[PDB]
Image: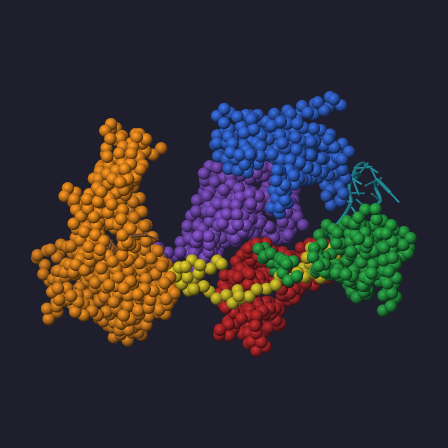
Chain colours: A yellow, B orange, C blue, D green, E purple, F red, G cyan, H brown
RNA sequence: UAUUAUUUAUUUUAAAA
RNA sequence: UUUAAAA
């Protein structure tokens, strides 16, 4: 919890609410996929993967 | 982007009914043009942040029209903005020796909000009506426009009042404020108010520091003080009448007998005196009867030592305490708040917004009706209040320490507490405390003896063969030496 | 160990030596006759280094063939057990090895007559079994002695020595504890001359103090050349 | 992105919160990228195994002048029961030592054969706590299927079986051994290991020809 | 895929050196005129000295300290070279000799030699610390790669600012850069690299060789000093063998260069600070009394 | 308004620098040069597209940025008149001008404009001209905006990158090279911004034509 | 068939008449 | 966990 609410200060909290800009996509997460297209080759990850 | 775009060019409108003026500020119609009042300012010499300004005019029916005028800071510092948040976090302005930390930018505190003379300035006026006994007949609160005629200092105001070749309307108004302040202070001391002393000194700069100067008091210092007290009392009653759940007030708890326990044991078994604890008036009257015939300063010493035994004043909102808990022990008033300093203190900023809601000037912000937010605000400004006091006492104590090593001399002082291996000496010349360890006090600390009941420490002084007994409340003489490879000794 | 005296007023260091005394220097030649053309087991103090020279030989692939000189490849293998704590392989630790290997190749490619051996390659395989400070200087001594064993023609000796500067006192052949407490300079002196083929300063040293450190550095390196030279005399006369 | 946050830890399941016959299924020819495909599945007791094998060959090696062919077998983890990469390559070298004695190498000069085995699912349903020995026989049968589907000459069929960590691969109806693998196990036992694996080898030797002659 | 130097071009440049002539018109001890340009965000610096152009980019993030030093912050640097600075560079060649040596020298100068205050980068000992990263982009290669890169990194670190942190008991809150203004890093001393190029027809040494002079070079020496008369780092390996007298002459000549370059970075930072703080005279909180 | 320069780098055939809002991209082009064995094309020109981030190493994010930038420049180059040759197009992102962890359209759009200008400075045979702009729509008031700021991206429902192909004096839109859209939108919003984008790219090439002409004309005779 | 050869050249004896 | 006033 790295929120300024835990400082228990009204001044710093009001300054945070005024200066904070909206970030719509910040409230969403995503998956970390690992693609493995078997094409009969060896080596590192293909540009396709 | 919160400050006014005009900057230094911001001016108060000459016609409050101007259509262009009211189009930008619709609340201008609810403002009382008081620029015909001969208002003056009394602040320390070389002051750029003027919060208060007084005026006095004799009504035709024998009474006086006394009115204090406070900077209309809440006209520029609006809630919900970064300017309000920056001032709420700072809580107050810290006043060190060399530097000074402001709560608000200098555009407001020095130019636009400060009640500068010869310029039209917005203000929050509190108009009274006093008789020949300094009794309030009726009080009225209003936002106004003023133009200060003069901006005297304390020394300049004391001269013009005592001057005999000036008898204009403004000068005669300053005569009435002096005769009304002594009558307000008279009934306050009879109500049980205290009279404590504070070692408040200020050093001068060009190196940089050279010497320390004790600040003398003037009759004008009490002139402004009694009306600043009267202004806060009237506003406290007003803002509590309108918002009894979230009124920004200040209280002072009664001191427990535990605080004055050790102090009375010292005065009884060394000076044969005591301090009454029945009521606040009994405590104040006992300090007046607590004086030494040989040391006129000893009376002020007891008043200083009893100040450390006093409870700490507290900011609070009215919804968290019953009305009998609003009592202020030190001022002996039923209810009190801070209002006459919105440039310095943030508590006064909340008082201005609440006072503007009682008059109907503008609706009170919802944040000042929230018990949760008001409780947090009160804790913060309380913490920032003590920190601002501890910062000033430490800056005066450090910058006077540079005067100890860079200016060797001998100064007289009084001891305030004795230990088994050290003495604490208070010096009125500098208003600071000094610890003298036993190792730096004698050549043989093993042959010393400490008597806890009589508060004395017997030791063989350095460069001396006769033992000296040092009791508490002794008028000793200390020196200053530089042993580094700053220090105070005992002459 | 613990809090120690680096250079006592009695002129004694933490390991007993003095300001101009080297660690014990035990070198060996022809230690791997059936695995390389040149072998040198370098034991300088607690440092234990195995240097193997394989060449000059035909390159495995013609992609690394020079028609006018030989190619010099130096491979430094720092074992996991060279220190007290068994170090785990770090991605950052690989960069420091490449800098050492390149500094060694550029150092000996100028002193080894590569023109005499055209269309060939000279592989230098190094294994550090234990390190205790001054490892860079000891790596140089192992390469010089291993190249001589392989009969590779060189212009002169290349002596490696490490010098530390503590306050105002320079110290020869710094060990691990001394490197952790002072600045260290490694030198590559060519033979009995005062010419440097390598100069690595990896810590801050005052400019007015660097002149004297180099003088005592090239001097102590001449002593290292003598210790290496004498080992070749004894190994040649007894065989 | 990939890998994800470094501060995250994998899920931990606690063991204290709430509480003859070896089935086989064979298929071949279903990957268009390679020449010969295979899919073997086996589910006995609380251990289910399902792996896929693909054969890409023979591939003409440019500039090569070898007399016989070169076999390249590579095991690759799938999605469940991940083994360490060192042990996978150990089984790969063991498998290459088997098919180099089975695949007609002299019939492929200047060319190589690349094998790809994907341990896509190795389920294990034991109640409460080398595990790779139970998959070596299933991998040998999968490669022989994909090698036969790829038109590659194989001197006789090759199969194997497990006998408490003991894996033995037979040839010529069990007349000659082509591979030996044994982890953990006990002592003295050897005659019963070669017997239990040989009967399991004949069970796989004819079942591979079943799906290879149909479809 | 390499640069071809004709025999006549090699002979002309060397003979010109024997006659105290450089094609660009500088002296043998003359450093190229450096030009520092700052971007919008903090830690964005572009260095131009001659036709050589390099661009640096500083960043930081919370990271785990080394268990050997739980009270120090980390410092990362990458000096990969793209084909943009010249088609002789292969993209993805991270282990090249130029890339490794450039990173190691700036790493020793900044991190090891105490130029960056790594102890000030400590948030929570043994758990939380700042990992200041320096990305170097080789835009145009006309020699002096590590010399320009060291000026870019040192200018970026002094221009970079990290988010603010408040200590509240056992809690630690990172203020967003939109609320509170970021805090600058701690820069003890300013190391500047100077590379010497040696030739032999009695040897000739030139300061900050161009790309053409760099290819005809017989030996290279890199020194790193600060205005405090301290030798931050020295790197010399192979080439023409030199003695202590020639080195000390290189160090004394380099000190005259690094001292002037140091004053320029300090001046160009002051000018950039005032450009982006126009209304800073009104926002001052700590002010003098009267 | 956008800023752009040409011929800034020395040791390459053609260079450029494109700036939009706060996004800065320096691109360099070298070709035709000798290709590698794994790069040569028997009949046409081979391209080597490289984009490098402003911070950190090149991740998989820049790999899809290369693949999109490649799909735009490939039909824009007359590859067949350079058989068995190579062209190295390298884009260096100086400042991202956007949140790298969330958006990458402002950098893709600038790399397209920087690569096209660098291809002009290099002298590669181009079939036509090109312009690229970023497009976004705001959540509260679903308004289409062209070249959105970094703050507007964090308050947008969908982001778009439009790359067009211009012929004949920069008036005829020959084709739509790239239209990359991510977020929330329907068929009506697509053609609404596509029509709006076609006239904002149309004034971009008109300004790009002026930029490159002010630089190439003093060079020639 | 080394006074022979390697084509984006792995040749490492091209000298004499 | 130093009363009050002006800074």
Query: Which residue is nearer to you in this view: A40 or E153?
Result: A40
Q: Is residue B264 left or right of residue C181?
A: left
Residue D59 location, quadrant: bottom right
Residue found at the very far left of the displayed protein: B165
Query: Which residue is nearer to you in this view: D66 or D69?
Result: D69
Determine the residue positioned at 55% across, 56% down: F54
Residue found at the very far bottom of the displayed protein: F188
Please state the horizontal and vertical placement of residue D88, each as a whole percent of the image.
Answer: 74, 52
Please state the horizontal and vertical placement of residue C82, each as a whole percent of the image.
Answer: 64, 37
Q: Can see residue B151? A: no
Q: Is residue A20 left or right of residue F217?
A: left
> Is D141 rendered above or below residue E269?
below
Please state the horizontal and vertical placement of residue B264, each as a whole percent of the image.
Answer: 24, 47
Determine the residue positioned at 52% across, 53% down: E62
Residue C132 location, quadrant: top right
> Is C34 rendered above or below residue B111?
above
């Amino acid at each position: 919890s790295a929120a300024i609410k835990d400082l228990d200060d009204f001044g710093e909290e009001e300054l945070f609410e005024v200066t904070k800009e909206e970030d719509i996509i910040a409230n969403y997460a995503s998956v970390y996929p690992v693609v493995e297209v078997e094409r009969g080759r060896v080596g590192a990850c293909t540009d396709e993967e | 982007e919160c400050l006014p775009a005009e900057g230094h060019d911001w001016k108060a409108p000459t016609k409050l009914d101007d259509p262009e003026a009211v189009s930008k500020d619709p609340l201008l119609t609810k403002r009382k043009d008081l620029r015909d009042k001969l208002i003056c300012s009394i602040d320390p010499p070389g002051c750029v942040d003027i919060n208060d300004a007084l005026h006095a005019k004799k009504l035709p029916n024998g009474n006086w029209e006394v009115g204090v005028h406070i900077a209309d800071v809440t006209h520029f510092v609006k809630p919900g903005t970064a300017l309000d948040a920056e001032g709420a976090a700072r809580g107050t302005s810290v006043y060190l020796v060399d530097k000074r930390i402001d709560m608000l930018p200098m555009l407001l505190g020095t130019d636009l909000c400060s009640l500068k003379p010869y310029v039209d300035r917005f203000a929050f006026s509190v108009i009274w009506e006093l008789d020949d006994s300094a009794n309030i007949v009726n009080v009225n609160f209003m936002k106004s426009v003023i133009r200060s005629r003069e901006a005297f200092s304390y020394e300049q105001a004391q001269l013009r009042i005592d001057d005999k070749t000036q008898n204009d309307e403004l000068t005669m108004g300053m005569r009435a404020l002096l005769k009304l302040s002594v009558k307000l202070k008279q009934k306050r001391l009879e109500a049980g108010a205290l009279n404590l002393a504070s070692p408040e000194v200020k050093v001068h700069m060009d190196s940089d520091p050279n010497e320390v100067e004790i600040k003398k008091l003037l009759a004008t210092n009490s002139l402004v003080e009694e009306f600043m007290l009267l202004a806060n009392i009237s506003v406290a009653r007003k803002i509590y009448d309108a918002f009894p759940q979230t009124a920004m007030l200040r209280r002072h708890a009664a001191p427990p007998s535990t605080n004055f326990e050790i102090l009375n044991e010292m005065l009884n078994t060394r000076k044969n005196m005591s301090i009454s604890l029945e009521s606040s008036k009994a405590l104040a009257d006992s300090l007046d009867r607590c004086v030494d015939p040989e040391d006129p300063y000893f009376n002020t010493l007891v008043r200083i030592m009893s100040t450390r035994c006093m409870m700490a004043a507290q900011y609070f909102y009215s919804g968290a305490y019953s009305y009998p808990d609003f009592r202020h022990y030190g001022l002996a008033v039923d209810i009190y708040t801070h209002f006459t300093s919105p440039i310095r203190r943030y508590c006064d900023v909340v008082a201005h917004r609440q006072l503007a809601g009682a008059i109907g000037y503008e609706p009170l912000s919802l944040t000042h009706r929230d018990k949760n937010k008001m409780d947090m605000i009160c804790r913060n400004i309380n913490r920032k209040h003590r920190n601002a006091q501890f910062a000033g006492r430490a800056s005066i104590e450090y910058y006077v320490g540079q005067v100890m090593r860079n200016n060797e001399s001998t100064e007289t002082g009084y001891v305030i507490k004795v230990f088994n291996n050290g003495i604490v000496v208070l010096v009125p010349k500098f208003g600071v405390e000094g610890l003298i360890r036993l190792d730096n006090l004698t050549e043989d600390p093993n042959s010393a003896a400490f008597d806890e009941v009589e508060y004395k420490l017997t030791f063989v002084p350095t460069n001396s063969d006769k033992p000296r007994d040092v009791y508490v409340f002794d008028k000793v003489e200390v020196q200053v030496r530089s042993v580094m490879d700053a220090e105070l000794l005992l002459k | 160990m613990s809090r120690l005296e680096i250079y006592s007023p009695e002129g004694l260091r933490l390991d007993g030596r003095r300001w101009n005394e080297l660690r014990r220097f035990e070198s060996s030649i022809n230690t791997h006759p059936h695995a390389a053309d040149g072998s040198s087991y370098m034991e300088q103090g607690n440092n234990k280094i195995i240097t193997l020279v394989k060449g000059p030989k035909e390159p495995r692939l013609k992609s690394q063939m020079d028609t006018s000189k030989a190619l010099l490849n130096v491979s430094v293998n720092i074992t996991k057990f060279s220190k007290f704590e068994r170090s785990k392989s770090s991605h950052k630790n690989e960069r420091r090895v490449l800098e050492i290997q390149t500094s060694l190749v550029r150092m000996f490619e100028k002193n080894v007559m590569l023109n005499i051996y055209p269309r060939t390659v000279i592989d230098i395989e190094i294994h550090v079994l234990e390190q205790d400070g001054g490892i860079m200087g000891s790596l140089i001594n192992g390469i010089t002695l291993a190249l001589i064993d392989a009969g590779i023609s060189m212009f002169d000796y290349i002596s490696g020595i490490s010098v530390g500067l503590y306050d105002t006192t320079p110290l020869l052949d710094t060990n691990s504890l001394e490197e952790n407490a002072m600045s260290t300079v490694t030198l590559g002196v060519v033979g009995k001359s005062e010419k440097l083929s390598l100069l690595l300063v990896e810590d801050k040293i005052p400019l007015d103090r660097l002149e004297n450190v180099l003088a005592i550095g090239i001097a102590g390196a001449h002593r290292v050349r003598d210790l290496m030279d004498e080992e070749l005399r004894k190994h040649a006369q007894k065989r | 992105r990939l890998l994800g946050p470094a501060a995250a830890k994998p899920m931990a399941f606690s063991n204290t919160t709430t509480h003859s016959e070896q089935e086989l299924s064979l298929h071949t020819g279903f990957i268009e990228n390679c020449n010969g495909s295979a899919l073997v599945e086996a589910r006995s007791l609380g251990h289910q195994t399902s792996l896929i094998t693909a054969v890409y060959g023979p591939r003409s090696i440019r500039g090569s002048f070898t007399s016989q062919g070169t076999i390249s077998i590579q095991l690759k983890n799938g999605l469940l029961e991940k083994y360490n990469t060192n042990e996978l390559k150990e089984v790969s070298s063991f498998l290459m030592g088997i098919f180099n004695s089975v695949v007609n190498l002299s019939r492929y000069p200047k060319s190589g054969i690349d094998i790809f085995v994907y341990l896509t699912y190795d389920k294990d349903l034991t109640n409460n706590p080398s595990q790779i020995s139970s998959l070596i026989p299933h991998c040998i049968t999968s490669i022989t299927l994909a090698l036969a589907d790829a038109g590659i000459e194989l001197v006789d069929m090759a199969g194997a079986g497990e006998a408490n960590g003991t894996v033995v691969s037979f040839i010529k109806n069990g007349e000659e051994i082509v591979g030996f693998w044994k982890d953990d196990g006990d002592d003295e036992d050897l005659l019963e290991c070669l017997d239990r694996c040989k009967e399991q080898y004949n069970r796989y030797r004819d079942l591979m020809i079943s799906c290879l002659m149909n479809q | 895929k390499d640069i071809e130097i004709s025999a006549s071009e090699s002979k002309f440049i060397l003979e010109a050196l024997r006659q105290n002539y450089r094609l660009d018109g500088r002296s043998f001890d003359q450093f190229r005129d450096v030009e520092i340009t700052f971007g919008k965000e903090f830690g964005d610096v572009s260095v131009k000295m001659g036709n050589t152009k390099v661009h640096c980019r500083i960043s930081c993030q919370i990271a785990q300290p080394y268990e050997d030093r739980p009270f120090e912050g980390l410092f990362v640097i990458s000096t990969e070279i793209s084909p943009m600075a010249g088609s002789q560079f292969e993209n993805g060649n991270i282990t090249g000799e130029d890339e490794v040596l450039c990173s190691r020298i700036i790493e020793k100068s900044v991190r090891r030699s105490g130029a960056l205050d790594v102890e000030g980068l400590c948030i929570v000992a043994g758990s939380k610390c700042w990992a200041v990263r320096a990305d170097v982009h080789f835009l145009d290669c006309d020699g002096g790669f590590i010399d320009a890169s060291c000026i870019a990194v040192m200018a970026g670190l002094m221009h970079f600012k990290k988010p603010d942190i408040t200590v509240h008991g056992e809690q630690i809150i990172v203020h967003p850069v939109n609320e509170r203004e970021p805090v600058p890093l701690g820069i003890l001393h300013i190391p500047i690299c100077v590379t010497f190029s040696f030739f032999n027809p009695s040897e000739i040494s030139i300061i900050d060789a161009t790309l053409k002079e760099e290819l005809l070079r017989d030996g290279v020496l890199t020194v790193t000093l600060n205005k405090n008369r301290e030798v931050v780092q020295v790197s010399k390996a192979g080439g023409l063998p030199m003695d202590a007298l020639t080195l000390m002459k290189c160090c004394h000549e380099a000190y005259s260069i690094i001292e002037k370059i140091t004053d320029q970075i300090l001046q160009l930072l002051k000018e950039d600070s005032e450009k982006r703080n126009k209304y800073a005279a009104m926002l001052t909180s700590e002010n003098a009394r009267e | 308004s956008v800023q752009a320069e040409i011929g800034i780098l020395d040791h390459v055939d053609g260079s450029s620098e494109f700036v939009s809002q706060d996004t800065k991209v320096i691109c360099s082009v070298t070709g035709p040069i000798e290709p590698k064995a794994r790069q040569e094309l028997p009949t046409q020109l081979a391209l080597e597209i490289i984009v490098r981030p402003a911070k950190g190493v090149a991740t998989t994010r820049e790999k899809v940025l290369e693949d999109k930038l490649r799909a735009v420049l490939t039909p824009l180059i007359t590859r067949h008149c350079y058989p068995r040759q190579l062209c190295q197009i390298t884009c260096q992102i100086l400042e991202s001008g956007e949140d790298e962890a969330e958006f990458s359209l402002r950098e893709l759009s600038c790399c397209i404009n920087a690569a096209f200008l660098a291809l002009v400075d290099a002298g590669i045979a181009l079939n036509s001209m090109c312009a690229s702009i970023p497009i976004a729509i705001i959540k509260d008031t679903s308004d289409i905006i062209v070249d959105p700021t970094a703050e507007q991206l964090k308050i947008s429902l969908s982001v778009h990158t439009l790359a067009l192909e211009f012929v004949n004096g920069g008036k005829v839109v020959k084709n739509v090279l790239l239209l990359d859209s991510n977020g929330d939108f329907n068929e009506d919003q697509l053609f609404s911004l596509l029509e709006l984008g076609e006239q904002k790219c149309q004034e971009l090439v008109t300004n790009i034509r002026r930029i490159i002409q002010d630089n190439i004309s003093p060079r020639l005779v």
